[PDB]
Length: 383
Ligand SMILES: CCC(=O)Nc1ccc2[nH]c(=O)n(C3CCN(Cc4ccc(-c5ncc(CO)cc5-c5ccccc5)cc4)CC3)c2c1
Image 1 (tube, rainbow, N blue to C red):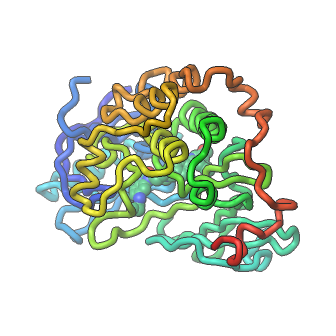
Image 2: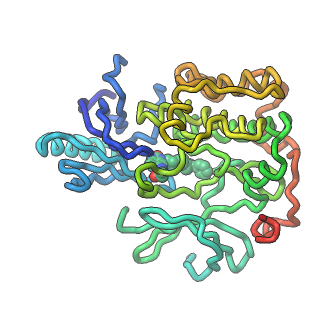
Image 3: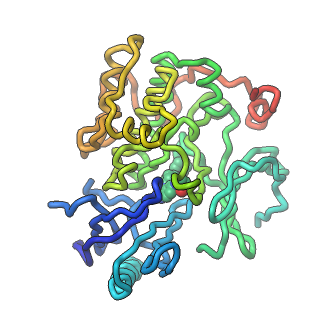
């Protein structure tokens, strides 16, 4: 359980596509971690950084002496692009990485679904809204290029996985209670009670992913939250890695500081996201927002988060801890992880086993008759 290789690499930023020097550790457990400076040295390894079941590619574009680690994590293809000064070093890194990966080695068809809407396109495939002909139920289908290659109440479940000759297809449930940004904008702001409920269920799902699955979600934002027919949260998994837009990938309003800086990150990234999401629910606006990306980054990195006079002291305490710039200081960034949030005064009185078991009654019931009611898909209502 030790280091197989370490040294400086040039890593391309995941959201700001610039080259940055980072000190990377390769460990026999499969973790490939990069730090801004050489670390003096959470202990539970995170699969986000694992090299297990990845393929290594050597390329001379966009830059010479580049190598790429490509991994399928759950239903998303992930790439990490690195550059070294010499081809001899690139060969050292790839073989070392490859050896570690080798050491860790030890019907339904497309015709059953009706294509409805394109939800998103990515470098390695697309996501479409479909309806199973037999049931009338709605699903998101991730169609990924084959060439490139459990269950929780509040995560969108992966139901079917099947293949074509050139595509790999993941079929996951699509909640029909409406997008959470659609509900928040309609009602402007949520009461602290209502935000506590959605917040509680998110904490429950994040606790599962961190403890049981040892994975950081890293994508927690309002756009990835939906309500099912009963009004419970569903965190979505409809994402696909895209080439940036000239070059920044997506929008940064929700990104944790340590993620923006391409620095070492862990489970604390999701608590930031929780803070971003709960700040907007209870305040009616994003914490940091400015059109200049140079300013948005500074705002996220530098500007101290401000609160409205309407927020209670408990809510202000929770948001302040969640939105601490430094993850080591952030609420939930310690070894207790999710327990720090659960035991917070803002969640006093919440029985956390009742949360996992959907015992808490939703404060808002979406106006749908069943799991197949298409109200929140209808154009007339969505506007
Ligand atoms: C600018 C555009 C772009 O390209 N962004 C980008 C680039 C590189 C990335 N590398 C990166 O890891 N992510 C990130 C990679 C993907 N996460 C999203 C994610 C993270 C974990 C699971 C997940 N897992 C395991 C289990 C069970 O076992 C269950 C789930 C699950 C299921 C249902 C709902 C919720 C979670 C599912 C999605 C967040 C993003 C990257 C993103």
